[PDB]
Image: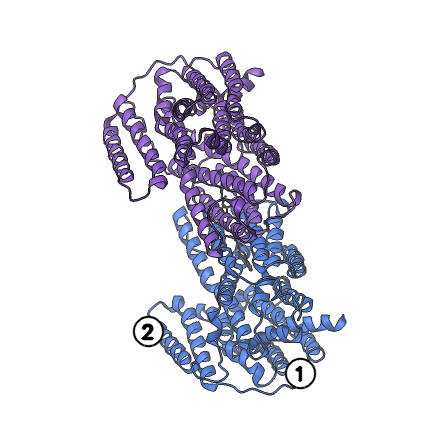
Chain colours: A blue, B purple
Amino acid sequence: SRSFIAAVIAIGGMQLLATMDSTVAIVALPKIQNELSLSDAGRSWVITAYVLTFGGLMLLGGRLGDTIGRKRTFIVGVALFTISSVLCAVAWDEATLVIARLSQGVGSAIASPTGLALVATTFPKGPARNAATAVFAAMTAIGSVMGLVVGGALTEVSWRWAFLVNVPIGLVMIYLARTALRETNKERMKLDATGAILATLACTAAVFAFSIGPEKGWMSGITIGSGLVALAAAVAFVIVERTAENPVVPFHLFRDRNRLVTFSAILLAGGVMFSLTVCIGLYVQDILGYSALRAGVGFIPFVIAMGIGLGVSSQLVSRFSPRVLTIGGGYLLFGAMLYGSFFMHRGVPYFPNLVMPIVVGGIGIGMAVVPLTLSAIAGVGFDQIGPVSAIALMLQSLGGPLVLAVIQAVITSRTLYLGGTTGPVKFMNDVQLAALDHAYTYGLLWVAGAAIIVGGMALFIGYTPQQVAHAQ
Amino acid sequence: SRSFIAAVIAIGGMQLLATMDSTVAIVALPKIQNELSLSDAGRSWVITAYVLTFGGLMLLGGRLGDTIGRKRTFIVGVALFTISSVLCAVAWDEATLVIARLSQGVGSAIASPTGLALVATTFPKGPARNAATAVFAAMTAIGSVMGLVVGGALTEVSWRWAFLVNVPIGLVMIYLARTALRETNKERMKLDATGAILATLACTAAVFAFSIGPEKGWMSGITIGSGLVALAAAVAFVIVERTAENPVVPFHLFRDRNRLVTFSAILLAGGVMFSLTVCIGLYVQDILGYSALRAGVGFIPFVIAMGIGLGVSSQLVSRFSPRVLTIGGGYLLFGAMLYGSFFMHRGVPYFPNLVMPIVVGGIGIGMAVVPLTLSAIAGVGFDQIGPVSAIALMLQSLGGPLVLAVIQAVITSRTLYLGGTTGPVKFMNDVQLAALDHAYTYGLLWVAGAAIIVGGMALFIGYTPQQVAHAQ
Ligand SMILES: CC(C)=C[C@H]1[C@H](C(=O)Nc2ccc(-c3ncccn3)c(Br)n2)C1(C)C
Ligand SMILES: CC(C)=C[C@H]1[C@H](C(=O)Nc2ccc(-c3ncccn3)c(Br)n2)C1(C)C
């Protein structure tokens, strides 16, 4: 009872912390610019510092779990995250802020992968694993909405006070991490230093190239050089992993078609969800003119609906195949994305027009999330959960930017076609506002079209409700 | 008053009669084969003579209404259909049945397209036209189900009495149409005999080739010759229509993207509806073992649901665009088809596994069909409505076989994949029955894919509610 609650909260705390930090950091960018006197490059670098280390230290963090221990790695990561958040709060110049953000991203990349391995190992297959997966999914949304609310609330005094909010809750997690999580005293495995180094180099180079491409121009020497470095590092990693004991990423796993389909669905679904949340935030905080507080408190129905959906999916996964639940959730998600696409324009009441799509989509996402997570880590084995979980988190965090960039490009092209301007929102006339509203409602259609493929690829799962939701 | 009801029922009764006769002809084939000792070729000729005469002379029937008179043409078509129905029952040799069916199909082709023209040119734009369209679409399914019931319950004594049920219906049509509909009083036009003859012979050649394809083969010289003749006839028709005084198929109004998209949507939607009806009837009769009478009794809720959907759509079209209603109906129908594809197999109870999908699909079809046809008959002209209606009915009745053949091919391939057998379903064991059940449940997914492409392509309609459902 109490032990299970403590264990699931300790496992899910890292996702809550990371999402809260990201949301609060993105909310209070321009007060930071005013106080620190930063340029556009500094504004980009503040967010880029997190992503560089988050992406460049994913597989390594997944592998160190067997090298040292999962519990020790979890507390180490949470402690580093808290210390680097304190450094972010105390940071006085641009260099200190960048260093602190890089350290916090290092802690996130060393702590997040181990959470999925912990949820796989601590609880065996059965109802306990289902409930743990539901809690793990719910913590992310709860953290996102809470971070949005607190960041909006703390916009009146200073941006420094916002980072310190990450200190107490994290400490609580540490306390829980010291009690519920146990150690099996299993034999300690080794690490493939060459493969891990190659993977880290390739990931860091790719992330740096992707971030610096649009900002400094494409094919600007640095961009192509970083791309070539990433390609060479990936090729060397693939060559090395062919005959290396305890691979960083086992390629022979990806032969099964069930797992390939599941992972591709994970990538696409993560991209769609990230694009949806970014677009809805921009539309609510830009077009309708809602403040940060109202935008934050308007997503509580989303949290409640997603929790209800996750609970229902956890209850019903023990008898129904994962593809059925995935398509069932997608049905309501696609209904909401169309209702919003057709009957949303500036000047509509919140209650009868905006909250119902939120509730329907949240319920659909609640049913959709659990079966994919259960299928990803199904029948994997202890000595191999690490890389699978690391790849799952990597794909979820990687699908986002590409789809978001495509949607923003479509919206910009539509706005240019309607007769608007690409300037700032705060210096816009009525015609440009109408053009932007129509462009956003048009981009929702492309998001739904992407969801079409996301769901159609999920018809080839093949898993049965006896390999993911029963004991042994 | 009573005049409105009389007009709408008289207009739709031709669709009712055609659908009922087609259903009762499909039902009573084995009895005719036993009685007349006809081979498979005889049955194929019997089923295909009506199709040949219905497709070959459709455009001529739609065009002669302007030169002769719409009311007079409808009267003549109904009388010819009644006489042919009387002749069909009292037959002694194969030739008599063939010629009676040919005459009946000729009459149906002459009379059916004039119904939509009468709807357009008799009831002014507004609520009256909406109600007329709703009832016109409703009694098609009403006639389908009542003809299925009559054929099931009447073929237990004598097959000849099945073809004698059309006489009272034809008599009430002739009386009501003579009493209610009134003369157009328009100046008589002139007919382009050469173009009409070319189009009629091209359509006849195409239908004959399609009929003789499966019976003979795809390599036989007869099929190649028929196809070449059809292509040459189409070339002659299109080249002569360059400077036709009263073109049979005007190409000058096909420069509107909305109209072309609407016509393609009509084609694909009609194909999907025909395929779904045929497949569900075959599934109910073959696998579940239901009798014809039980199937007829079990589809009355489909009629009721379609009526409810039409009633709601007629009122809703006054304020919303065709796109929104079409997509909502497609949403409900997609949900119903997915539920059928997943949770259906032999041995299930009838009540909570077969009524809800039927009702939801009926509501969706009702909400979907009305906006499409109002879009089809919107803004054409008093001198070109006939050809437009003829093209609409031609595409609606032509889309069926094209997709039904593909669906049946997929079903047979899937059946052979699991290792079933080909032939009669009554002589199979449990293995082949299970294989064929899985094949039908798999083909439902392809029908759903056809529906989703239908909706995606109908997303580009672009009409305005004012031009379709607003008066003056
Ligand atoms: C051909 C076919 C069966 C289409 C199905 C799509 C679907 O079911 N689409 C879907 C399903 C699930 C998710 C999702 N969302 C968040 C997290 C995980 N999964 C998403 Br974006 N789209 C629709 C309902 C249109
Ligand atoms: C991208 C997009 C907007 C997809 C929409 C499809 C749709 O809305 N599909 C649809 C819509 C209408 C009809 C129909 N059915 C009978 C008679 C007339 N129309 C049919 Br088959 N499918 C779905 C709900 C998946």
Whether A8 is drawn above or below A268: the answer is: below
Q: Specify the amino acid type for callout 1.
A: Glu
Q: Does mark 2's beta carbon lie closer than 8 Å to ligand 1? A: no
Q: Is A201 situated left or right of A92 in this image?
A: left
Taking the spot 76% from the left edge, 70% from the top edge, the residue there is A1
SS at badge 2: loop
Residue A436: percent from left, percent from top: 47, 50
Whether A398 is drawn above or below B138: the answer is: below
Whether A290 is drawn above or below B400: the answer is: below
Q: Give the residue number, with chain letter if any, for mark 2.
A: A221
The chain letter under disc 2 is A
Q: Residues within 10 Å of mark 1 (few under 14, many from 20)?
A: few
Residue A120: percent from left, percent from top: 62, 73
Q: Which mark is residue A310?
A: none
Q: Is B108 situated left or right of A175 in this image?
A: left
Give the mark toward the camera: 2 or 1. Answer: 1
Residue A99: percent from left, percent from top: 52, 79
- A172 or A126: nearer the eye? A126
- The CA distance from mark 2 to mark 1 is 49 Å
In this rendering, do the residues under marks 2 and 1 share a single chain?
A: yes
Q: Give the residue number, with chain letter if any, for mark 1.
A: A183
SS at badge 1: loop
The answer to which image quadrant residue A239 occupies is bottom left
Q: Residue furthest right?
A: A1
- A151 or A364: nearer the eye? A364
